[PDB]
Image 1 (cartoon, one colour):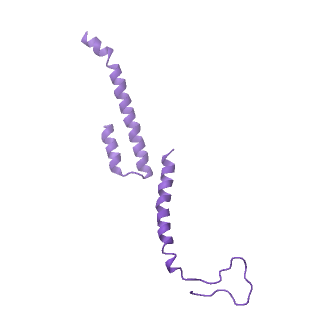
Image 2 (tube, each protein chain N blue to C red; image 1 turned 45 degrees about the vertical axis):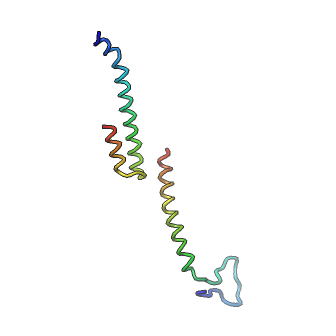
Image 3 (spheres, chains in turn green, brown; image 1 turned 90 degrees about the vertical axis):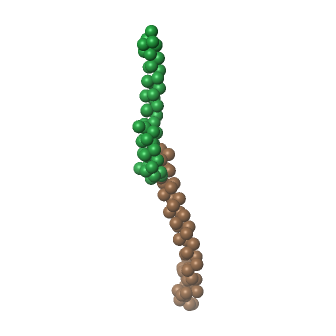
Length: 53
Length: 52
């Protein structure tokens, strides 16, 4: 029964954490766009990589 | 006044440089305004690419 509970609600956690990884990934992509344009320095891009990892 | 340029008693056109008053104190703020323009121009041309 506890395994059926985990199979019943771990999908609604894995989809949420995958959306979190995708949101942080496109956050890092926007921070890399800001860096390669030249607005912010390299340390904010390293903070974006810290959050994505 | 540094140098008179026109020929006296001659014809002038609409916009001929007659005299040349000393620009030593009115070019040394043009460099300041040009430096501020060279900063804000690069900032605006980076934000124009970054808004897209």
